[PDB]
Length: 373
Ligand SMILES: CC(C)=CCC/C(C)=C\CC/C(C)=C\CC/C(C)=C\CC/C(C)=C\CC/C(C)=C\CC/C(C)=C\CC/C(C)=C\COP(=O)(O)OP(=O)(O)O
Image 1 (cartoon, rainbow, N blue to C red):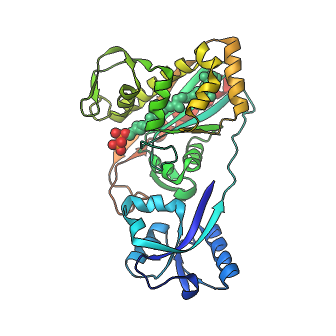
Image 2: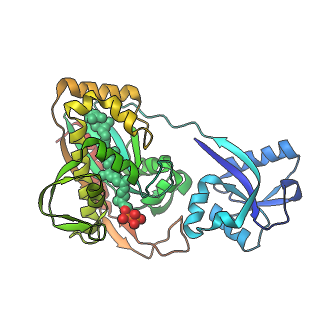
Image 3: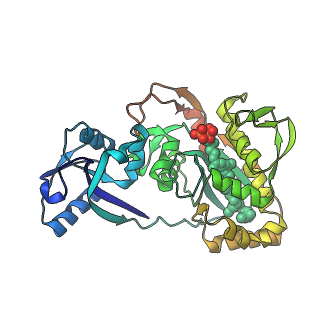
């Protein structure tokens, strides 16, 4: 993966280059490794020593820059998308006078040592190309036991107030924000929360979802409550419903009008996962899995190795047999009085986790993995 650290000044600054500076403001408390590599690079290429004025975060550095309290900041490009949350026009306010590119070797998928594995499904709140950055409003863990032919779907509410890994600095914030830092942040956040290994991920957005449902010929679900979606464009009666791509997207997005609100939306997403799995495990879909990869690979990101896909597909082609699917959701209490790490100046709704629910959720994941009752 690729990111950059830059030295940024205000767009209209007289400063043109780093040799004109004596100090820079940077969050060395939380991004010190990266910051020190940038400073060493500046020393190497420009023979310029800079002292650091410590900021509490990249957001804090940005605030100091626009307040005119510092002349220059360090900016790590990952954190641009976080700054954008409180300051949507930040890009127009700054210029970059020095740039250093970075690469982080990707954390490999973990092959499970037994019959079970966990796949994390991240759904990103945007249309367009898959590289588009946004929050992850779908966060479903699929625990699959190939020996017992059981799958457990664990939904964690987008607003769940949890320690956010990596860029989140292990500070509490809504889970959906982890997806802005990147899929690694989402994965490690949920690994930490549930005490489990996540073997693989799949990341997709609105446009990805539409393409996938299109390719599979729609999906079929049993709808439990009458509702409408997308400012009344679609109406879903009680009973068996076929969903084409646009209908399915409406079906998984509506929450406010549902009897159990976001929990019912989570359940509707689980129904749609089951229906997708039913299409994906048809003899035709399995035989044609390579065409499905070819058709969706530009819009769906995953670290499931090709090798593993071939094993999963062919084992299913040989054996048949459907997976029994069960579902659960992490519960808690909605509050508007708890601080957001990413958006410290905003009052956001978050869901404070219920400890007893967390214990139950963890025990159910372990039971399915171990092939227990
Ligand atoms: C068959 C095979 C491959 C193998 C054999 C089977 C086997 C042995 C195992 C199975 C496992 C494997 C390896 C593969 C199968 C593929 C799997 C596991 C899953 C497929 C399902 C999938 C990839 C996605 C479904 C995700 C889903 C339900 C929804 C995504 C919708 C999106 C992107 C966003 C919605 C965001 C929301 C809720 C609100 C924003 O919207 P809002 O309007 O509120 O906000 P605003 O827009 O206004 O801001």
